[PDB]
Image (cartoon, rainbow over all chains, first blue to last red; front, side, top):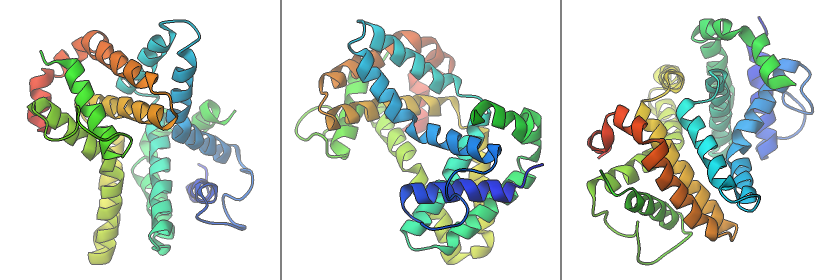
Length: 147
Length: 146
């Protein structure tokens, strides 16, 4: 199994720099050097930009053909009630963790960042060990999200 | 059955006002006249402040009982994977619709506000009618969230 530590740290570090809470070298700096890392980055970016893309799509449709925007609204709304893949809750979790880190840096509790990551690693190692391995493992994840 | 148009108007108007996009008389300004409306407003408030309240609770564990902070994170994470009740998806739908309207105003596309509200009403009355009935009807929602 992949080094969860290095995954968590790449994603969180990626997000912190993206948002401007951190800078310079270290994890999350420049491109991901590991397809699992790249897949999680992409999963997280997709997750956080979903609302904005949806709005633009609906605004666009509003003058493709009539009824077109309403039909797309129905399709996207259906997803809220179906849900996304189960892998979606893992993406949600990483995004949640990274947001906890960002707020930490924002409220001047920098050491909280290091411990959030540690809590993340440990949760994935113990709690989701079976959920992850079941769903197809990290390899399956990297296929669906990584390109 | 509740007046869906009025519920949608109240919730979206409440949110637009709460975030400063509109002001003045109209749905969502002032007390809700219908218990279902008040329940949805409260549901949507809880939903949209949940991250901030979670961060507040975690930071307070650190500032008070650091030893049980990891436990708390695990509990919240657990809850995140369980994935809440059916009604939580309906709350998410109302929050989503309000966010579309808010973004329509922000982006100077006011027509879309009226269109999104009509789409929400049609969705609730037709597409989601069975799902709401199955989940126990509007009365149950109101009881749970009000």
